Every structure is written in C-alpha cells, then in structure tokens.
Amino acid sequence: MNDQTRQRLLNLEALVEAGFAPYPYRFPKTHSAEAILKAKRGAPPESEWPEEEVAVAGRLVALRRMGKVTFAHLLDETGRIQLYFQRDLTPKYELLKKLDVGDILGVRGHPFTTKTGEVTVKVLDWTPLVKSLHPLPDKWHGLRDKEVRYRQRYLDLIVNPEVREVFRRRSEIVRYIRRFFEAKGFLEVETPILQPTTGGAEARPFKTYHNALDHEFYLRISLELYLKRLLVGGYEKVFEIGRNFRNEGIDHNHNPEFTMLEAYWAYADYQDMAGLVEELLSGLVLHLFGSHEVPYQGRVLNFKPPFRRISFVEALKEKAGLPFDPLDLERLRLWADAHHPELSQVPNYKLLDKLFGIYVEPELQDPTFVFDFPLAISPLAKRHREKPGLVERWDLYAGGMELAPCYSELNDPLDQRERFLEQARRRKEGDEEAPEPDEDFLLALEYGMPPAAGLGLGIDRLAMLLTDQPSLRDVLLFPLLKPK
RNA sequence: CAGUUGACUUUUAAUCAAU
Ligand SMILES: NCCCC[C@H](N)C(=O)NS(=O)(=O)OC[C@H]1O[C@@H](n2cnc3c(N)ncnc32)[C@H](O)[C@@H]1O
Image (cartoon, rainbow, N blue to C red; front, side):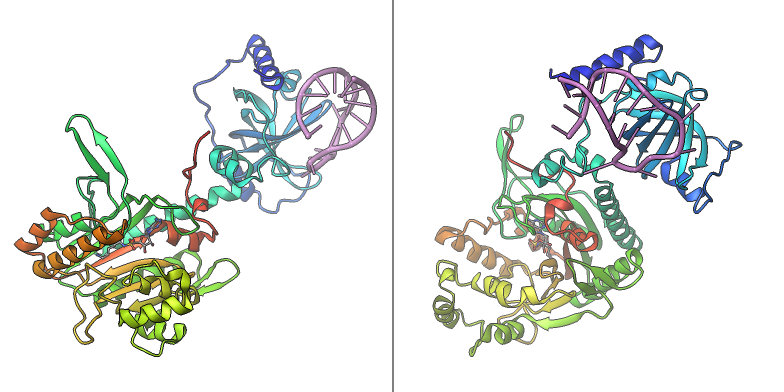
C-alpha cells in the first residue's frame, strides 16, 4: 500500500466514524446530469428553482474547495454537472474535506444558475457512496498512452466521455441491422463456436481441448457452414450476429476476435441480396446521420443509392495495367514476379487477392460493389452463367476495406467436393489459411440445399466507418493484448 | 505531477501559501 492510497482510506474512516456507511447498497437518483442541463437550456444567470428538487449520482471529477463555499463537478453516465456547497446550508460541510476526486457521490438539492450562467445543483444533502483509492488521471497528462487506454478502458471511459458515445453508436448500428433483418422475415439463430472442423473462409483456427468428451475442438472461423445446414433443414431465411475467431495477426482492419453477421436467403441470387444490402446500409447511414454522408478520416463517403458497381477483372486489368487476361495465372506469375518481387512466394490463386488489394481496393472509398470474382479465390460460389472462369460473387468495399462478401451459394455437392479436394491439395502444397473439408457439410449438400444467396458482414469494420475510428481497437470495448 | 499542510461565503485546469 502506497501513501496516497492509504490517505484515501484514512478519509473513509473519518466518514464512517462521522456517521456515514462505508459502502451503501443503493442511492435513489431521480435526475440525470444532461436532463437537468436540457431542462434549463439557456436560463439567465443568478436564477433559482427552489420549488424543484433533484437527486443525482456520479463520480467527483473536479473539487474546488474555497473555504466556506465549495464547488465540484459530478460526472454521471450522461455528462458533467456542477455542485455547490455552503457552510450554513449544506449539512456536515466540514466533512466535505474528507471527500476526494474520484469518489462516487450522491446528492439531493435544487437547480440554480451561477453568476457566470452555468447550471448548478445546490447541495442540500450528500451521501458518500464509494471511496476511490487512487487519483483520477486527467486528460492533461494521465491517459494519452493508447495501450494503457485499452488495458484500463474503465479509466478511459472516466477521462474521455467522448469514448462512451462510440460504443453507444455501435449498439444502435446492430439494433438497426437486427430490426431490419427481423422485419425482413429472417430468423435469428445461434450456431456453435466449438466446432469439430472449420470452414467458410481462409484463415488459421484456434484450438482447444474438452475433458468430458476428450477431443480437440476448433473455434469457429465463420457462420456459413451451419447456416447452410439450416437451409437444407427447411428454414428459408436465417441470420446470426456472433463472435468468430481467426488465429492471425492484428492491424487496423484485422483482429483475432471479431463480431460479424451472416444472413441466408433461400431461392434467391446474389442480385436479390445486393438490393437488400443497399437498402440496409443506405437507410442505416440516413438514420444515423440524416444525410447519406459518412465522415471518415477527413473524407465524405457517399452512401446515396444506387451504389457503384465494378467488375473484379476489368477493374484490376485497368488499374494494375495488365495487357493480358488476369485469369491466366501463368502470365500473371510472369508479370507479378517482375513488377512485384515481394509477391514471389505468394501462391498463384491468391495472387489475385493481393494485386486487387494493392491496385483497386484503396481507391474504393465510397461503397462499391465488386461483382463477378474469380473462381480461383471463391470456393463456395456457384459458377458465373456467362463468362467462364468467374463466379456469382460480389464484395462490398468502403473506406478502402472489405465489408460484406456475398456469394450466390453453390448447392452442387459434386462441384463443392472437388473444390474442397482442390483446397485440400493447397494445404499439402503449403497454405495454412486454407481449412479442411467438413464431411458432414458435404453430406448435407447431398441431401440437397436449395439455391440461395448468402451474405457476410464485418460488424466491427462497419462500426469503424460510422463511428469514424482509425484502428479496430477503437470500436472494440476491451481489446486483446499480451499480458505482463 | 499530486498529496500533505493552512488560508479563503460564486469559483470553473479556482488562487495563495507551506513541506
Ligand atoms: N456464403 C456467403 C459468404 C459468407 C461469409 C464468408 N464465410 C466469410 O466469412 N467471409 S470473410 O470475408 O472471411 O468474412 C466476412 C467479413 O468479416 C470481416 N472480417 C473477416 N475477418 C476479420 C477479422 N479478422 N477481423 C475483423 N473483421 C473481419 C470482414 O468485413 C469480411 O469481409
């Protein structure tokens, strides 16, 4: 125990001996800080409302003791509200010197405006709820370090009330997304995180052991496979907003653990789903902001429908400056190895993802559909019905990052199995990201999955745009870090 | 930088003073 910590405890003892309880069970708060401020919006200075009564409760952020009159600022959930104390008015005024900054306080009184004009709660009765054992770090010199801000988000939320509104806005996004799919005739569902075998995307899984069953399971990397099984089952419209786990590095776009949505629509193509996602995201922004304009890192992202639609091949061929057909992997190897020697030990199929990610992805700041992906990098999308080599798939980009991939689902078992067999070769060759074949899934397709359109959507990434954050850790409440 | 210490009956990164 240090000195300051001990000094706080010595003050607690004084308050306990004085008569108060050390840690009360409850406080009957009647008003919130912002509700008082909103009520007296633009009231003239030196006003009073002794008729009215209020009771607030929060944390002491400031404390300006000026002899026989004391001031303070109470920080609740909503905002800051000023307190006023006086000797021949507030009971046990002497014992206000045993309060410290950081303590949780509850007060009763009436509202009034100072000479300056700020709305203030005239304390007629106070109750020390909690005694903080450490000093509050100010915005000035305490919490500027980003990593300490993440480790102690509680401290962050005290110091920076701006951070509070980020996660509130995050919640509203989900609520809107949910209400949409709910009202659009989709069923919310829960699939297991503990899977025996993974599949749905290219990533390395997490592993874990279970004692009762005595077998090594994997953490789910995608929602697809099990939602696909429900389609086979009979459900036509399903969706889920669950946590997924990919054992990979960390950056502004990628985080090992992340929330993401997946909806599925029986007897529909990727065109049908495209119109839905347009209505979703357009209305979402229009609801949140009021315009179709999303501030993100000093840019105005235009979500006015319809969204711009480009082809994967045509866009790459243009912006990468390719004289040949990019689907030709042999010629792309030549071009790549010469122009991009860093993409030498990258496999031939992934060479498209990497090149598209360099030349095309960053230019897509506005919401842009990227229709007609290659077959090489799409194992779960039914083939294109005109151009050979491509599939019915679109990925929605915005802010120079992928939001929502949407295949037109492959329901042919024979085709699917041979793609899983192709995928199984790539793992033997040398590819950690390519998962293994789910045999039970392939069987589920054999019994017959109806033709459908599946959606994916990174909830965390969509948050970053709408909440306007640089890194992904800024839209995660408690990010993962290496302990010490 | 806070805490301590004592001052101070509309201050708002309250101020002065003491260690
Ligand atoms: N059947 C149609 C496709 C279904 C979705 C598909 N199984 C899938 O998971 N695709 S994904 O691209 O791997 O993930 C979908 C979105 O999830 C987001 N995502 C993916 N990996 C991460 C990570 N690591 N962190 C955060 N967000 C992530 C991102 O927006 C992706 O576009």
